[PDB]
Amino acid sequence: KGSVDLEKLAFGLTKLNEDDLVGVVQMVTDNKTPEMNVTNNVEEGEFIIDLYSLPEGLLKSLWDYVKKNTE
Amino acid sequence: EVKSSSVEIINGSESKKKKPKLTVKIKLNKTTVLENNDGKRAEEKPESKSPAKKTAAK
Image (cartoon, rainbow over all chains, first blue to last red; front, side, top):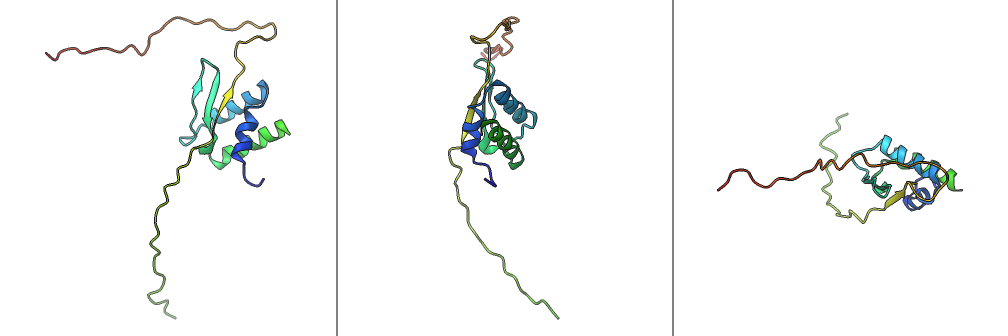
């Protein structure tokens, strides 16, 4: 994978434990761009975030993270 | 030498492929059944987005 499989990214970050998925939600909100479609519902405690609109910089940083966190 | 009147532009066309985007709902670990830790309590009912109906238009 030279590029990021957006499917393995999505399904890879939501399968994680607290420390891992929290690290995910913090990276996406820290560098929140006008493209990425985030919706933090604090009631259910969830980040409904569209990774498809993440820049290459973010979806690579997140991929590297969640892939070494799962594999 | 002279380069001359070379290189014509190419007139292309659009392609509307927006596609259903792959969104994900990352579930954060809120106050559930877990080990000995105290959670949170609501401050008050603020009603910050309180709507209003009309003022002067008879």
